[PDB]
Amino acid sequence: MIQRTPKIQVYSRHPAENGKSNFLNCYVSGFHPSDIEVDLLKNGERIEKVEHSDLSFSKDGSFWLLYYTEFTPTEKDEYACRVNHVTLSQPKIVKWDRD
Image (cartoon, rainbow, N blue to C red):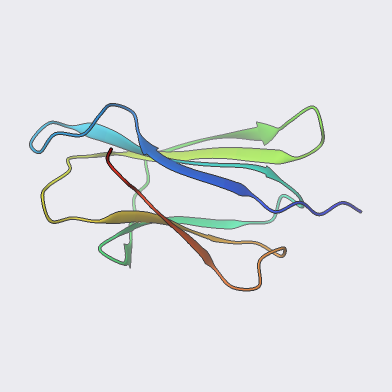
């Protein structure tokens, strides 16, 4: 058996501007086993519809997921990614930051 803690990156496809559509990405990678729970949060609340999920095993046997959705940032909305995995003692929250 192998277990490996996910790497978690949260970033937009383009630099952000209010009014302009964009995409918010969670790239969760290098983990094992493949069982995992990954949510995008908007103002602390789970985003139900996350349009896209690209995912696979890597050559090294670990797993990766790109979890993303269209979003239009505003001044006052904060976003984060919440991940749970057997390697984590509690859920891991990674905030989105622009820059």
